[PDB]
Length: 112
RNA sequence: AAACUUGAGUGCAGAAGAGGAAAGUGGAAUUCCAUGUGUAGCGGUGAAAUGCGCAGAGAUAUGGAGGAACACCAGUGGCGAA
Ligand SMILES: [Mg+2]
Image (tube, rainbow, N blue to C red; front, side):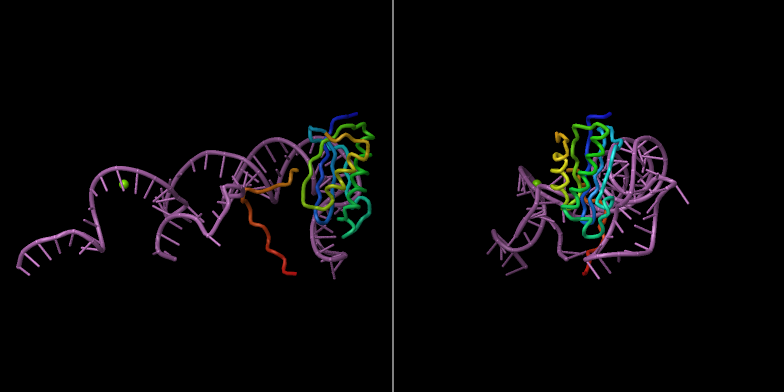
């Protein structure tokens, strides 16, 4: 039984991943678009992200979690959908996208 | 040959600068490593597959190693012969 928690959202252009934990960082339940049998372009849709945070939150509340914080990441479109649905699963809502200070060289641009 | 001070230098008084060389200090991020939680995919594309993963990945939290580069400031802004 844990009541205070943190919800991590990792939304990219290929997949949305949600991990729920306390403030101590130890996870309790996670889901993703792939865990719901979505493949490819389906795995990145904003609708398909909400089906993942809803699944994740229901498992964390089963442990007894009521208040969870939000840490969002990535430019994936499944950001509002995965965050609003956090408040839509009986969870009380009380940006961590890594930016470098000019560090490592990024890969070459794609000539599609 | 002799004068001159405008050109060109010097002196004096101010100011600005990513100009150069050397040695130090620091924060973010990437990768790898370890540890704790924790479970079924992660990753990737037009769509896929190769690839990694149940021997515990990816995610998350903490710590460590190492190299490289210096967000914001930042501007037909500045400096330099290039
Ligand atoms: Mg002077």
